[PDB]
Image 1 (cartoon, protein in one colour):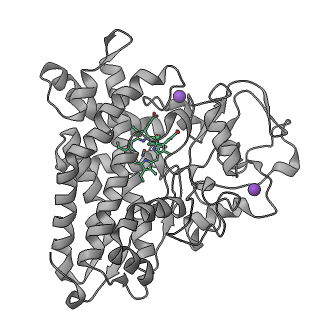
Image 2 (tube, rainbow, N blue to C red):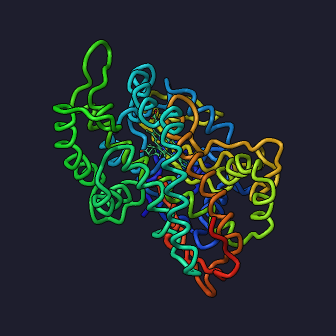
Length: 405
Ligand code: HEM
Ligand SMILES: CC1(C)[C@@H]2CC[C@@]1(C)C(=O)C2
Ligand SMILES: [C-]#N
Ligand SMILES: [K+]
Ligand SMILES: [K+]
């Protein structure tokens, strides 16, 4: 379904890419997006899909636009337009300097000191989950680890019952990879309706959990409102329940096909943080964007006020101008260039938690289950959206080649 080409967009810039169903998806989702970086595609193109919008395809442009909030506003950060307009999460839907005081509060609840505090629980849970799976000789990695590991850690940090995971995960997925069953607004509304009474309770009787801390924080000299707290907590849920989950699956899928990469990390685990960065580059998975605040000429292209521009975080590190042989996983790259956690003022608040979860997973999985593979004749399907994902990842292994610690 192609929207009529706006008069200001010249035809040579048209490239009808569908971010929710890219044509080359069967080759892998990153590969499907990388079609935007072939020699036939300009640096900045207009797709008529999904209501019509720009797509920047090169790291330089993506970084520049994410820095220039004056022209590229986060007030409407999702495609399609109806989703972007309904989007009111905090701090993401705010530009500097307004986002600042809310972002400071986000850092308080998901930032570094919180990770270096929950680290024992993170380590504990990874070991527990992996040891439980180890003697089976198989698992569906998405449901058996990729979901419960980061999600249970998030529910712990937020003080929310694990029994609510299925419902919350469903709603989160509707916002990033919609199925058509409900509008963005309806999904966001269901999430908000869940949070509303919980926020009320925790303003009545504060705990030390993330929701309590947000709901009782302060902005420009005054208490945060219940509305503001809801809008921030909603974003924390979306951010805690989707990205790391899917990232872990892309990474484990790769490791399942790459015995030599597994051994690099097992033999020299001090390389694990660098490997984490390289996997974050190669299997980058987010693509949101911004809205034009005014008419603006950007790299020779006339953008109009109100035009949406997708600035795919995924693409920067896949750009061969940023990394040579970008589709090759090389743990020894002298610089792993990427914007996987975003760029500019909205650079991911949870990136430290994410990295810790990834690094713990790499170490603890490979220690106990050093040799595994994708199940014979299994077809792995990826899905694409604001956050791209892995549908299922059936893994197999010989339990005789595993180790308890
Ligand atoms: C591999 C894992 C992750 C990736 C790839 C990722 C990616 C991103 C990206 C690209 C953005 C910027 C979006 C924009 O500029 O519009 C962002 C923002 C954000 N993320 Fe993550 N993220 C990850 C993990 C997490 C985790 C574990 C949390 C914990 C709740 C989290 C919470 C947030 C929050 C609260 C923001 C908003 C920050 C702001 O607007 O100032 N993320 N993330
Ligand atoms: C694009 C994101 C990854 C970022 C955090 C969660 C997410 C889906 C948002 O709505 C902002
Ligand atoms: C962030 N997700
Ligand atoms: K291009
Ligand atoms: K909006």
